[PDB]
Image: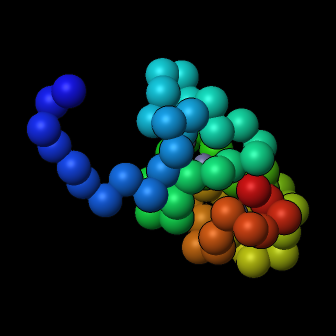
Amino acid sequence: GSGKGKGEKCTSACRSEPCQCGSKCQCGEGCTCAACKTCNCTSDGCKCGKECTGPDSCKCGSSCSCK
Ligand SMILES: [Zn+2]
Ligand SMILES: [Zn+2]
Ligand SMILES: [Zn+2]
Ligand SMILES: [Zn+2]
Ligand SMILES: [Zn+2]
Ligand SMILES: [Zn+2]
């Protein structure tokens, strides 16, 4: 409809509300979506080992164990 086109690397699922990217995460790296692009590392202990210990301090991509 609306004549527009940006670099949407993310899938329709990710671009939905709420995000439907799930754990499969078929979107693109660079969205930092707070649903799929999350981190399971806690401040108590890093779950992946990248020492990110939190999504807000995450430095590794979505193909990581904390994702
Ligand atoms: Zn998403
Ligand atoms: Zn995603
Ligand atoms: Zn995305
Ligand atoms: Zn992480
Ligand atoms: Zn980690
Ligand atoms: Zn990680």
Question: Is residue 38 at all visible to an observer of this figure?
Answer: no
Name the residue located 56 percent from the left edge and 34 percent from the top edge: 13
Vertical relation: 29 (above or below) 12: below
**Residue 9 x, y percent position in the rendering:** 44, 58
Is residue 27 shown left or right of residue 40?
Answer: left
Q: Is 19 placed above or below 41 here?
A: above
The percent position of residue 3, horizontal first and vertical second, equals: 13, 38
**Residue ID at (24%, 54%):** 6
- Does 8 sit left or right of 20 as displayed? left
The answer to which quarter of the image holds residue 36 is top right
Residue 42: image location, x then y, percent: 77, 53
Q: Is residue 18 visible?
A: yes
Looking at the image, which is closer to me, 4 or 59? Answer: 4
Residue 7 horizontal/vertical position (percent)? 31, 59
- Relative depth, front residue between 36 and 21: 21
Choose between 36 and 5: the one closer to the eye. Answer: 5
Q: Please identify the quadrant where the N terminus is shown.
A: top left
Residue 42 in the image: above or below residue 58: above
Left or right relative to 5: residue 54:
right
The single residue placed furthest to the left in the displayed view is: 3
Residue at figure coordinates x 50%, y 36% from the top left:
12
